[PDB]
Length: 378
Ligand code: B12
Ligand SMILES: *[C@@H]1O[C@H](CO)[C@@H](O[C@@H]2O[C@H](CO)[C@@H](O)[C@H](O)[C@H]2NC(C)=O)[C@H](O)[C@H]1NC(C)=O
Image 1 (cartoon, rainbow, N blue to C red):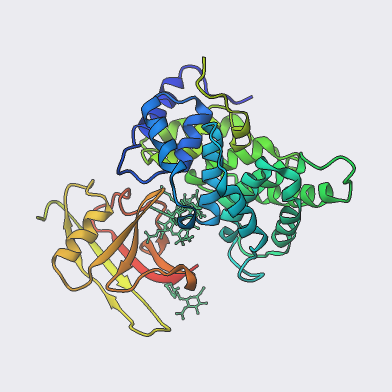
Image 2 (cartoon, rainbow, N blue to C red):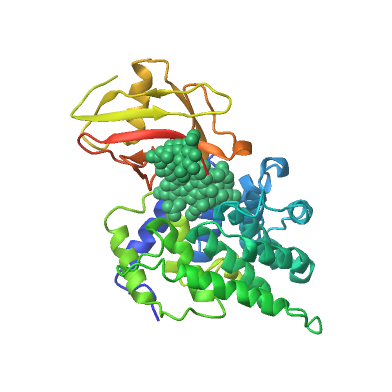
């Protein structure tokens, strides 16, 4: 009802190639990219094989609940036995629970990914965990996250459709109800322009909407959203391979639920712009900061990361560390104080007062932008 117009296909093909082309021996092995190219039908068979091998050999002790889920699905989409990882994931999940009943919505993202994976390998063995998961989700009150909601509906839809014959005890009722719940919250996060939540959460939301068993009261204009996406691509919004990985499936009319059905082997300085960069902190382990600066970055371009690099050059001791992930460079430490996920604490970036929608290697700061780095919690 809202496929990509065969006229815009070249556009989709292009980003697919951009995304596959990012796979290299040093590149961070991204399971979402593998899933995406496999659901789309891979172009570059060497990149396909390389990534598949990097994941087959990933160490189970290096992966988080969500990594694990993603990696199990990626291998499966490459028609490779995940073996070991599913057992490991199953037991970690029987041991999972949120930090509290007021835990942030995104706390559920990884677990959603895991349940989806486990659901694909053995639905019945996953009921216990999924029932518990649905109840925990039903009980949470935090402000809604579309990305998480999307993942959660996929996982629950997977279960919803695999209710064991004979085992007829409101499991369907529970999952259906929580799904209805989430769809209502996903809808109503739907802008008039077609965006759902935000651009980088729209791809996942499209998968969820095309797959929940029960739509929301307010109808969703699918075409309006896919058209908005195509235009966004044409404006250079999807240059991040991970961002391509999250919309490609939708653009090809597939979702993570199609993974099990994948067919394999198919037939130093200054310049022109000056930015104002503040770094902050307020705390427990004391050590409070609050120091500004003005940086001279090139043209516009020199991503917001050049700003941080030059600021470290002036050496006001406020240097930093960066850590690699599926989305790119994450600023993990500033002036000798790291993120530490145990304390649900990290560095949040913002323009003025509003948080950035892109990372430091992607964002392009304007004229005299005041970009702050508050060390908050989530
Ligand atoms: C949870 C979450 C966070 C938490 C992470 C907790 C944790 N360490 O587990 C925290 C609060 C730290 C965070 C921060 C930010 N995030 Co965030 N985050 C998410 C979310 C909801 C789920 C990710 C996840 O757990 N995936 C499952 C696991 C298993 O996969 P993973 O690959 O291992 O996940 C890792 C990465 O996703 C990484 N990560 C999280 N956010 C970001 C952002 C950037 C720019 C990068 C490079 C990496 C990164 O954290 C995980 C640790 O490895 C996503 C949604 C999505 N679509 O991906 C948004 C999302 C990835 N985040 C986003 C953004 C923009 C940010 C920030 C730049 C916001 C800001 N500060 O202004 C900050 C940047 C931090 C910094 N200082 O560099 C955007 C990215 C858009 C883009 N880059 O084009 C997304 C897509 C949300 C959206 N729809 O807008 N995030
Ligand atoms: C920067 O970070 C601080 C602390 O993380 C934020 O201040 C908190 O504001 C919240 C409001 O949601 C209060 O409940 C907390 O008590 C405050 N924290 C502290 C340390 O007292 C501050 O608002 C953030 N600045 C932004 C987003 O511009």
